[PDB]
Image (cartoon, rainbow, N blue to C red; front, side, top):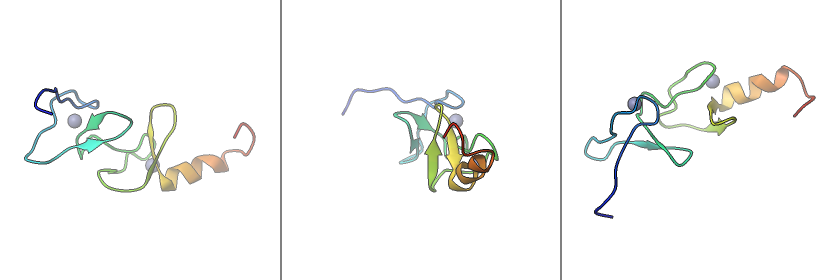
Length: 72
Ligand SMILES: [Zn+2]
Ligand SMILES: [Zn+2]
């Protein structure tokens, strides 16, 4: 509501732009900051995954598997 504090988990600065901000993993990141951990692709608005408190784009998430079926 009225009270509350903002913040960008990525850089740290507050996230505000007249209706701007990417919420993921119970956190807030800037459209730019919010990106993959492998290819570091712009995930501002797309399908991604969550592994080890990280962000992996569908593409990567699928690529990582190739590595090996064992251990998930
Ligand atoms: Zn940021
Ligand atoms: Zn990726």
